[PDB]
Length: 308
Length: 303
Ligand SMILES: C/C=C(/C)CC/C=C(\C)CCCC(C)C
Ligand SMILES: C/C=C(/C)CC/C=C(\C)CCCC(C)C
Ligand SMILES: [Mg+2]
Ligand SMILES: [Mg+2]
Ligand SMILES: [Mg+2]
Ligand SMILES: [Mg+2]
Ligand SMILES: [Mg+2]
Ligand SMILES: [Mg+2]
Image 1 (cartoon, helix red, strand yellow):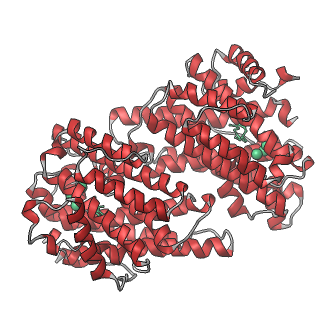
Image 2: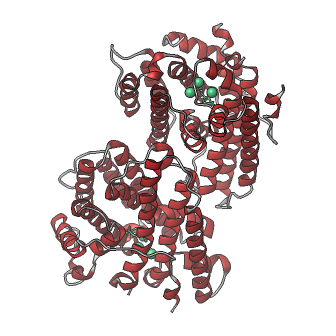
């Protein structure tokens, strides 16, 4: 049971609003037309709101609902990228991303824009009511880098080229949109970090470690379904190619890198400099937020139908 | 004492063969926009050292941008506006509008017209992705300048940790590093541009450039009653002598140089093309480290 080796020296939590928020995410998906014909009875068991509830457990219900709807949006987009033809067609992906990028700049969707474009416009509108311009620009750029990473994946599929470990790990930090999900922690915890603390090297390194942990945990849990689709965006498959080793050996190596990255995150937590009382209180809420996300990803993924 | 002679690097810089005509054109450009002994400024000779392999057109943009930053900085650091947050906010709102692409008007100051000209010229050489990254680094520079202003108004000195974290933005070095891509005509993919070791190399280079400046600029900053200087922040935190504070600053500078050259040897192998472009970028960071020191040691600005 290699899944038992996905362990952390810290624990998570879930919002008491979990089920209400999950029901509302399904209703939101239906409203914006994101539910496919093949998802009729499967829709019930997606449980995207139960991931959001674990990721942002202290959030007010309104803010948690934006986070839940955003997480649903990312799953709907991701299954298009990873399980349909658009993920093998760079020109179709560029055309769609041009529409998403226009909407992120504040453009209103046109009559013939697709469901995902309208849904993204709804999330931007709702975040604009809750967040200042500074935040919206930072979130938008993390989302742009996620689209860039999806186009990078598409070229890999079109070329039949598995990236090396160094390239994969560097790109994977963007292909999961985890940095955009970290941006929501500020809104959930209602914290305003000053520029010098937000961008501090140790904070960047804690964010990088948490992102790696989440993505490599996902890779160990999602390699079966990704292999079923002939995909190559997975630390297990990337390690297997680089080392020319067995699948068990690649899984063992991936779980070693995951365990090492957890110890790096725990180590670097004690390396946050003292700025002042107020900044360090806010900063500790943000880093606690990263820990809730690490736990949310594993806790939800171990029980989710998505990886069954 | 010869403490300036301890600012050494285990590498050398270079200067563009176009240095003087660019310097003369920068001085002319500054006069044309009314931002302006003038011949002693030599802002073009900093740009020529920072971007030594740049085509003349691109070097001229970089030179006019460096001149702009110096003109802005002397308003912030030697003028009343740098002690007035409401007046700073008002001016920044006009800059942030021009950066988003808004046309200047009759009410806007010389710096606003000059910034609009630079954004126009950069928009002809760089894609939207670049303009956004550059604009955000400039935005963070303005934010750092307002942080400086509140420090002056409240007469507060930040601790070493706070000063060093903020100083990475108060110098606009990251905005200057963005111009390396255009100077070298390289396109780094997202995963390499934002890689942790690249970020750590940029941070080390920025710290080196800023702390070198601090050691050379503490006298003129003391004369203006300013406290945005590693030497002065160390003096306040450790309650030590000025010589001890300078020695402490130079030890941190030397350590950061050792960190930069060590982290160069930790750049991963992505692929042949990406690593070719990356070495041009990182070499660019080294040209900037040498440019800052080489120019500053002979500049009348720090005489
Ligand atoms: C982001 C992807 C991983 C694996 C980490 C957390 C999952 C999230 C935030 C929702 C899924 C968004 C898609 C990219 C699948
Ligand atoms: C940036 C500051 C240092 C000390 C190195 C490079 C100098 C430059 C790029 C212009 C000087 C004006 C700025 C302080 C606004
Ligand atoms: Mg994916
Ligand atoms: Mg997927
Ligand atoms: Mg996966
Ligand atoms: Mg100054
Ligand atoms: Mg200054
Ligand atoms: Mg100075």
